[PDB]
Image (tube, rainbow, N blue to C red):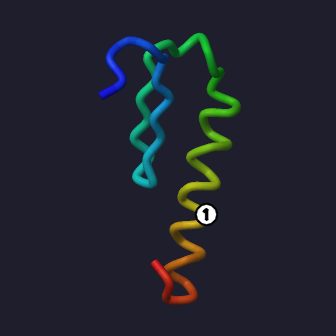
């Protein structure tokens, strides 16, 4: 859909990540992103809203 106009930064709630260039973002932010994603997933299931 986007061709090669933009670089892609894809993150999933099941810890699967996909970057077109890894040297864009270091494993610091990478982990911070996947932390929040799973934190919200567990938070939503805890209060029955997932």
Which quadrant of the figure contains the C terminus?
bottom left
Q: Position of residue 28 (x, y in %)?
A: 70, 30
Q: Residue at x 43, y 47 (%)?
A: 12
Q: Nearer the viewer, residue 50 or 43?
A: 50
Q: Is residue 42 above or below residue 6?
A: below
Q: Residue at x 36, y 24 (%)?
A: 2
On screen, residue 33 versus residue 3, left or right, reads right
* SS for dot 1: helix
Q: Work out which residue is located at the far bottom of the displayed protein and give it.
A: 48
Q: Is residue 10 above or below residue 13?
A: above
Q: Position of residue 16 (x, y in %)?
A: 39, 41
Q: Is residue 47 above or below residue 38?
A: below
On screen, residue 10 versus residue 29, left or right, reads left
On screen, residue 1 versus residue 23, left or right, reads left
Q: Nearer the viewer, residue 1 or 18?
A: 1
Which quadrant of the figure contains the N terminus?
top left
Q: Nearer the viewer, residue 50 or 7?
A: 7
Give the number of callouts. Answer: 1
Q: Position of residue 11 (x, y in %)?
A: 47, 41
Q: Residue at x 56, y 55 (%)?
A: 37
Dot 1 crowding, Cα within 10 Å, few <14, some 14–19, many 20+: few
Q: Residue at x 48, y 17 (%)?
A: 6
Q: Which residue is mark 1?
A: 39
């Amino acid at each position: 859909k986007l061709g090669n106009s933009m670089e892609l930064m894809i993150f999933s709630y099941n810890q699967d990540y996909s970057l077109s260039n890894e040297s864009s973002l270091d494993e610091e932010g990478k982990g911070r992103v996947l932390s929040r994603l799973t934190e919200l997933q567990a938070e939503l299931s805890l209060k029955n809203l997932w």
